[PDB]
Image (spheres, coloured by chain):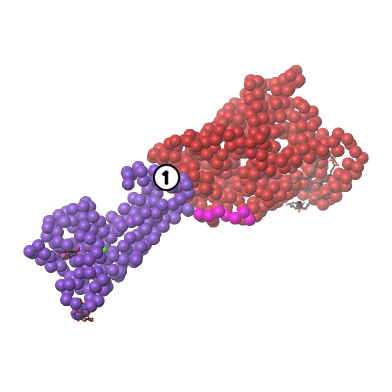
Chain colours: A purple, B red
């Protein structure tokens, strides 16, 4: 798409025509090539708890996961990492590990990203996948839609009720703290910052 | 008064409400940042070359008034009569209307944060300032001058805050609005001419510099030295305030802004942003309270030649104030704000003022061929009133041949309507003329308790 100077020339050009610019923001997960995840799986410093890791019993090339939770695109939502020798959680794909939002260091890093783009002059944000932000820490199994189905065959996302992996207690308070961070850039009149959420 | 304290009256009179209102319409006509700062410097040159021409006439002739004794010595009684008529109904009430409308733009704007305040609130708060200042100055002759010292003190505090905060932010590297300063401009003689109208409104007051600054320890040296120092010091403050605006604002954000200083004070002074609508509003009614002091000085000397109604410039017996002249200026100023619109009263004021600025400066060149043997202590080089005459021809003819709007027709039709009154009341002393005027003079005298001023010329 270009460089950072191409973005800054676009933001200035949008403002000279009287337009506003909002961008997407992805708080739920990163790539597994992010620098936080490469430090997380070697247990380096504070980054050890940036992602959700749990013990598993990977043998014969196959993983026994800690529970029955499924990915949105459909298989187990736990993936074994060979360097860490633990399993990490992902809501969408195994290349997209979920951030641990019960860690307050993670919540501080998301706020610095928001301040970065608001300083560039972005007029607002669209928040993606906010209902996936928190999961239950008790790690109990979800309820099957068909209770006589054998659990070896439960692999599709629509075969479970997602009572423990979507819309947990404390999720709306994280979205409200995002609104509080953007309120420090909204005090000047005519420069209110927009926050929209996507939950489909 | 010395030299250094002579600068203080020149700066304090010129710096007013103009620098808080005019930067939007100078930029709107020359649509780049680069030519906008060239215009604010070129109006500082016109204001000092114009005030040097008035300093020569003010020590040559030595009669009080304004441009009225300068026009009488050069052309006769016809353009002298037209000046006292056009300053009675056009020049002085529109100056009072622009300032009181400029006060109301700054009181209303912090209550409409991202929004535009409706015209009924701007006009009915400006009308309440015209009536309140006309009531105070018609009752309490000493009260207007005591509060003037705290209005001048509040004026140059908010000027020093804007200039210094613009130099601090420019030091930190906020120079990205001056990058390609000359891309997108107008070489149009209607857009350049209207940027000169609004730029010279903020410099207005250079022609009233003659009389109250003759009280110096050594005139004919300290008066032309107070103009070369005093007005280019104002030009240094006006360029620095406009540079201070463009460090926090784009040229697009400055056009889409109601009051340009409340936008500055919202980005720089956040937890105390209300001090900019508080000090600018104090500085603005200080500029309107100052003009009601000298109400009647030109009225008295034009009435002495029979060129003005003498019921004006009468003095109330209780509360020794020129109450007929103050009440008359308040009525015409409230009539002017109902069609209203700063950027329409500025063009209406500037067409009439610069028609008569260029007639007295041309009268300086006439009085060198017709009026020798006349003892000139201050003497300018002859090229200074020549180019100041040709620039005044450019500021009069170019708006009506490029962008002729309807306010330039009402300004001509009000000046030449005085030319009819010259031929019915001055040139031909008809019998039915003073059968009307002295009944009005006698009945207004008992209605207001106003007497002839117990005062001869000096
Ligand atoms: C629509 C277009 C046209 C609009 C015209 C509107 C005219 C409205 C006039 C309103 C006058 C308001 C005066 C009150 C101002 C008070 C200010 C103040 O503080 O005063 C202190 C001053 C102090 O007096 P003290 O209280 O006695 O000490 O108070 C007064 O002097 C009040 C006296 C009232 C003056 C009224 C003058 C009216 C003149 C009308 C004459 C018209 C003649 C026309 C003849 C035509 C012949 C062809
Ligand atoms: C307190 C405020 C009101 C007091 C001042 C106004 C007095 C009310 C009377 C108004 C005029 C009445 C008709 C004229 C009476 C005098 C005629 C005459 O023979 O003069 C002899 C007169 C000499 O009279 P003497 O003073 O008695 O010697 O000769 C002249 O002075 C010639 C100059 C005339 C100037 C006329 C000024 C008219 C002011 C009103 C203009 C109205 C339009 C305002 C602008 C449009 C709206 C934006
Ligand atoms: C996970 O889902 C994938 C679907 O992408 C399954 O992998 C293959 O799916 C294709 C159908 O598109 C079959 O033809 C292959 O036989 C599947 N592979 C295998 C090894 O069976 C996969 O079975 C699912 N389950 C797991 C545990 O990975
Ligand atoms: C899902 O639930 C159904 C019953 O709710 C389970 O049982 C099947 O029900 C159908 C009803 O028409 C019968 O025809 C089948 O014989 C039943 N038995 C089977 C398929 O073994 C069903 O087993 C559950 N699981 C799945 C994967 O369908
Ligand atoms: N005689 C007058 N008060 N004229 C108006 C002066 C305007 C002043 N120079 C300003 O900056 O707004
Ligand atoms: Ca999550």
Residue drawn at point x = 70 percent, y = 24 percent: B364
Instruction: Assign the C terminus of chain A to one quadrant of the image.
Output: bottom left
Residue drawn at point x = 21 percent, y = 57 percent: A95
**What x and y, as percent, mark residue B186?**
55, 35
Residue drawn at point x = 49 percent, y = 44 percent: B252
Please tell me which residue lies in front, B134 or B397: B397
**What x and y, as percent, mark residue B367?**
73, 22
Label 1, ligand 5: CB separation under 8 Å: no
* Chain where mark 1 sits: A
Q: Residue furthest left?
A: A60
Q: Is residue B18 above or below residue A123?
A: above
Using the rendered view, name the quadrant where residue B81 is placed. top right
Disc 1 crowd rating (10 Å Cα; few below 14, some 14-19, many 20+) is some
Res. B136 in view? no
Would residue B125 be found to the left or right of residue B90 on screen? left
Using the rendered view, name the quadrant where residue A135 is placed. bottom left
Ligand 4 quadrant? bottom left
- Magenta segment, which residues? B114-120
Res. A22 in view? yes
Q: Which residue is mark 1?
A: A12
Say whether residue B116 is magenta: yes
Residue drawn at point x = 23 percent, y = 58 percent: A96
Q: Is residue A158 above or below residue B426?
A: below
**What x and y, as percent, mark residue B111?**
54, 56
């Amino acid at each position: 798409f270009g460089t950072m100077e191409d973005f800054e020339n676009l933001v200035a050009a949008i403002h000279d025509k009287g337009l506003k610019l909002i961008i997407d923001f992805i708080p739920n997960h990163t790539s597994d090539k992010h620098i936080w995840f490469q430090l997380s799986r070697t247990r380096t410093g504070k980054y050890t708890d940036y992602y959700i890791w749990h013990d598993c019993t990977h043998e014969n090339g196959k993983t026994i996961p800690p529970n029955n939770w499924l990915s949105v695109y459909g298989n187990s939502s736990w993936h074994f990492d060979e360097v860490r020798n633990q399993c990490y959680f992902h809501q969408f794909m195994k290349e997209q590990p979920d951030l641990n939002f019960r860690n307050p260091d993670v919540q501080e890093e998301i706020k610095e990203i928001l301040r970065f783009w608001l300083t560039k002059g972005v007029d607002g944000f669209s928040l993606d996948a906010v209902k996936f932000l928190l999961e239950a820490k008790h790690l109990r199994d979800e309820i099957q839609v068909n209770k006589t189905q054998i659990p070896d065959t439960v692999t599709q996302y629509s075969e479970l009720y997602h009572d423990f992996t979507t819309t947990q207690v404390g999720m709306h308070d994280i979205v409200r703290s995002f609104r509080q961070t953007m309120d420090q850039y909204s005090t000047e009149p005519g420069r209110y910052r927009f926050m929209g959420t996507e939950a489909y | 008064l010395g030299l250094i304290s002579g600068i203080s009256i020149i700066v304090g009179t010129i710096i007013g409400s103009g620098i808080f209102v005019s930067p939007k319409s100078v930029l709107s006509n020359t649509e780049a940042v680069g030519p906008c700062l060239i215009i604010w410097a070129a109006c500082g040159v016109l204001a000092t070359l114009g005030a040097l021409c008035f300093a020569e006439l003010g020590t040559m002739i030595t009669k009080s008034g304004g441009e009225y004794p300068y026009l009488m010595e050069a052309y006769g009684p016809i353009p002298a009569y037209l000046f006292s008529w056009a300053s009675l109904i056009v020049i002085k009430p529109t100056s009072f209307a622009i300032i009181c409308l400029s006060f109301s733009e700054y009181v209303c704007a912090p209550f409409y944060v991202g929004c535009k305040p409706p015209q009924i609130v701007v006009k009915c708060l400006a009308a309440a300032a015209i009536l309140f200042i006309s009531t105070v100055n018609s009752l309490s002759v000493r009260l207007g001058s005591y509060v003037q010292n705290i209005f001048t003190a509040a004026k140059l505090v908010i000027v020093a805050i804007i200039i210094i905060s613009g130099l601090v932010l420019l030091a930190q590297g906020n120079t990205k609005n001056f990058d390609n300063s000359f891309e997108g401009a107008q070489l149009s003689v209607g857009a350049i001419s209207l940027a000169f109208y609004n730029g010279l409104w903020a410099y207005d007051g250079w022609n009233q510099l003659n009389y109250i600054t003759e009280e110096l320890r050594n005139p004919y040296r300290n008066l032309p030295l107070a103009i070369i120092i005093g007005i280019p010091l104002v030009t240094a403050c006006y360029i620095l305030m406009n540079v201070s605006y463009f460090t926090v604002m784009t040229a697009t954000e400055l056009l889409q802004s109601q009051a340009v200083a409340v936008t500055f004070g919202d980005r720089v002074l956040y937890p105390a942003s209300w001090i900019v609508p508080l000090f600018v509003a104090f500085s603005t009614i200080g500029a309107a309270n100052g003009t009601c002091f000298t109400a009647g000085r030109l009225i008295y000397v034009a009435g002495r030649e029979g060129h003005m109604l003498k019921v004006l410039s009468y003095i109330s017996v209780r509360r020794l104030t020129p109450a007929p002249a103050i009440i008359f200026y308040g009525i015409i100023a409230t009539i002017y704000i109902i069609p209203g619109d700063i950027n329409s009263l500025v063009n209406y004021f500037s067409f009439a003022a610069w028609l008569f600025y260029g007639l007295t400066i041309l009268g300086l060149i006439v009085m060198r061929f017709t009026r020798k043997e006349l003892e000139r202590p201050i003497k300018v080089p002859v090229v200074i009133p020549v180019l100041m005459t040709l620039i005044s021809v450019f500021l009069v003819l170019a708006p009506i041949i490029s962008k002729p709007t309807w306010e330039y027709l009402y300004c001509v039709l009000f000046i030449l309507s005085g030319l009819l009154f010259y031929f019915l009341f001055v040139h031909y002393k008809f019998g039915w003329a003073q059968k009307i005027s002295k009944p009005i003079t006698m009945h207004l005298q008992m209605l207001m308790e106003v007497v002839p001023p117990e005062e001869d010329p000096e």
